[PDB]
Image (cartoon, rainbow over all chains, first blue to last red; front, top):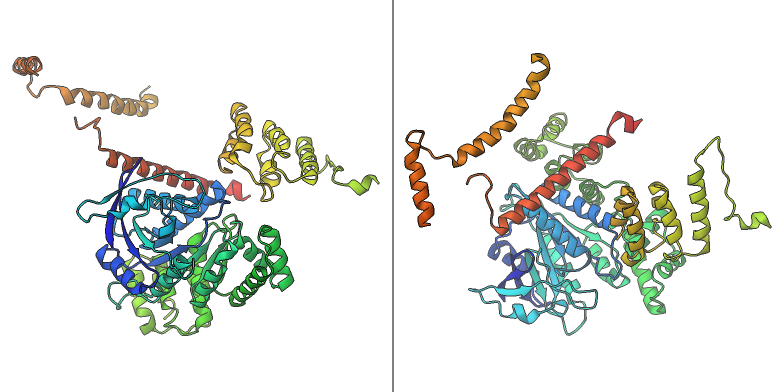
Length: 374
Length: 97
Length: 91
């Protein structure tokens, strides 16, 4: 089910898509993304897990988040996994991605916004149902209100239209989780010689209690999460719990009730409390991003990844991917503070490849650091 | 009984602050915040802050998390800030919905 | 007067050079007294029927507008960052 979309409206753009069922293997979709659509394996994957709630971010925080994400992503080739629906934070994030793409004087590195959207949420699905390979389907762009049905965003280059599973109404979440897990087990390069394991990272923006199960499943899959300090939903609960230092069942219940007065179900409240406790039990996979304080998303992403790697193991070869990513972002301070601090032994054979990468990509600070480190 | 209220009492230290307009605005916004949490209630204090170019005080007190702000609520205050040549408040309102 | 004027004279020369080049754009390539041939040809073409100031396709125009907006945002961000790191602001 491959087709092309020719969005018609203020800006005429061409976008690809593929229909898929929730029972498919994510390996096939990854292969079709890499080969059929010509997308190079990303050097960074940032998945959005929010912004579909009625309450939306303030324009200042929305702009700060989009600028930080685009600035972090533009160094390398990154993918931004969002629900390809023209609404909320997703619409503006796709707008920022397309604005960067148009203004990008270097097409070698490309920031691609992939859209994983449910088939039940698509407006005018019959219009794209034609999907003639010779003649791309014409799709009209309409800025619908919240409601329950949205239109495909024109700014998203590629789409993954998942069909709703008759078993449970969570097919899109399961597909997103499986896709993130599968992508996290790939190599960022064409060959496994100078390639890193793809850094998959999730971002939470004003989540609802319904997505707690998917978030915990992702955490079980061992992929880091970033929490906006001023998002508003479950993100506020998590940042308040982090500020507390410790989590208690009564405390988390009280915060959940205060933040979500509408939801009052004893079984649901208990399940959400248990899910939140189990999520906070990990901790090392959770990291808070405060745009009012830090406003440097790349630094926080690198810190979260290096924290996860350090929690995983102490071997030098394990830290290699994080060090290479730090090289690619000129974060010599972060690398010196985290990776090259006492605990990890560093041999010349271990550092030869990273030395090559820093030397080719014109990173003098990392060259100095590696020469000074063996 | 006077100290029992407290929110209606505010201290002005000319040796420390010496900015009477700031203290007046702080007292009024404190009283309004103690009164209620609705956006429409905060409207008069926001308009007065607009009239005094106290963008810092407004940002610190009125536009801090607690109060939701819709475009329809902010349209009149946007008009007032735009007519009276208050660019800081124009920037704040554009950034706030 | 030379010392005070020379620097402004250079800028004024550049500003006038723009207009002179604009004039030379539409000037016929034949110098006088030959120029009469070009004038007759132009009159005949008008009776029978630019590298500067060009009009671009919609897609390219939108791309350049977005690129201008991105560059403006970068320039403003640089100004703000330089303001934050200034000695007076730090003090």
